[PDB]
Image (tube, rainbow, N blue to C red; front, side):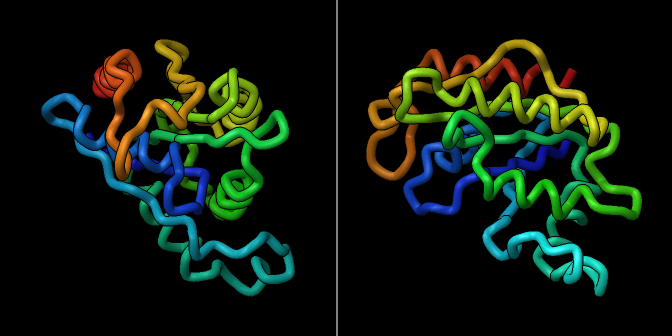
Length: 174
């Protein structure tokens, strides 16, 4: 089972990217996570789209098409999804036959804030309706006070979080 991990943050020390990197080693046997790189995706402009998909967007769409499931790591800024993540989704969601259609998925997120990306997750779930993506409802993974969840580089010190992430991946497999 091929899972495409999508981090909504571009910063080097991203808690969400670190969560996905850790997730790669928490999958059950028979499953593997490949990471999407959305750093080359430009801000959306219909006038640009009309001339064709930028190479970075085409690559992203190709990865989504090839994936059996999706794993979103969504940062939360100003009580909603990070604009960068939404922008990437906006690009990949364009016609023809946008690739998110029918894909099962899991959502997780990390934030320094108290609610560990909860608000961004429910907004994303609304967006997923239009894309016809089917996200797991349980378990939910909202890592709060993320500054204390990781050490050097990006290892998870929160075993509870590691367990829940392990559960989502086991759910996608099923």
